[PDB]
Amino acid sequence: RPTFYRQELNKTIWEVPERYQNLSPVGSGAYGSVCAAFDTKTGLRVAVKKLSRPFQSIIHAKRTYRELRLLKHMKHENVIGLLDVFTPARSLEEFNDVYLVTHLMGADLNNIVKCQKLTDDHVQFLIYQILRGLKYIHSADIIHRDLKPSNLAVNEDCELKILDFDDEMTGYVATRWYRAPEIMLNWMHYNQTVDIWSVGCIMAELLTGRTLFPGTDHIDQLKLILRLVGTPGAELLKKISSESARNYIQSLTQMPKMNFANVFIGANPLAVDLLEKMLVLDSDKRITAAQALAHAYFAQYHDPDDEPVADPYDQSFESRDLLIDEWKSLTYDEVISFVPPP
Ligand SMILES: O=C1Nc2nc(N[C@H]3CC[C@H](O)CC3)ncc2CN1c1ccccc1Cl
Image 1 (cartoon, rainbow, N blue to C red):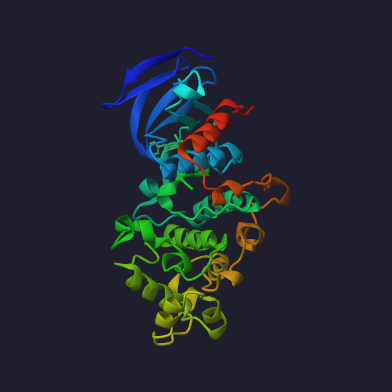
Image 2: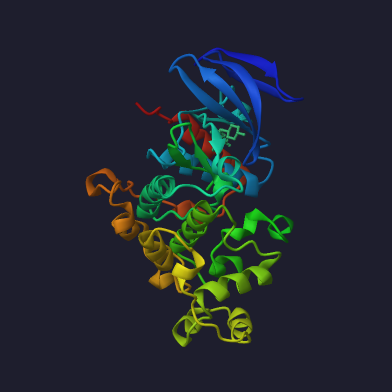
């Protein structure tokens, strides 16, 4: 057991192993505050997230377990993984805090590309890495569900990692602009292809410097989407299990799909072709990450032998109802059994 020391970081008392030094706030994280630090044992700049009240409720305790389980599973260059997880607690009885450690990323995509049109080569590379990470994530039957520029971190080398797998979804907000229509409007049980829709939106924005579907609200956004991809056909309509949603869709005037070559004027014809394959209304028909990687647009980056898949991921716990202390004990076992990556 390492020796821990205490430090107050913005009215918060952090207790971390001595190996972590120079803790400095970098902002908020998903359900916890994040500090950048230097891991003297590995020489890595890391981000340390102290979870806020990890076990205050069943929902929080299960979310804490979920995040730890997911982070402990993700081992891929284009996905945020775990370098360390610790608690100053000496026993399950005293267990109350959880700290998660990851590589420190330089900036999120949003802050880098905001209002800026990128060069085709840069788009090729950024999207290639997103799809490579997605192939890995999807191979484990994991769906990201909230892919957007702010959840994509990049370093100075444009090296990219996917991270962070309602009032905040209302209005003119980027929190909803990259969502596939079927999840935005709860049309049906959605699959991993919702993530491909998000990549298409991100890719279009990198190419034009403009949000693809910057709706002022959910409906305005759907209209922007249908004007581009066309209103659904009978085949897709049958798949919208939500009768309410299906019924509203049917009230819209039919529109044929636009010519993407005339929307993305001047864009590489191959980028155009890939966008048309990702931004397909029917999720059953969207190109998969594995198929997209093999698309000619990524000819200069694709390598079938360097696009790994993940080990199987058991998420049977998602359908389990346990007590706070049971989720807490399962989380403790996962913290205690953690083995750092080489
Ligand atoms: O929340 C997180 N934020 C990060 N930020 C940066 N860099 C930021 C980018 C935005 C900039 O404004 C400040 C530095 N790098 C890595 C993470 C990792 N990270 C995380 C995810 C899951 C579990 C634990 C953690 Cl710490």
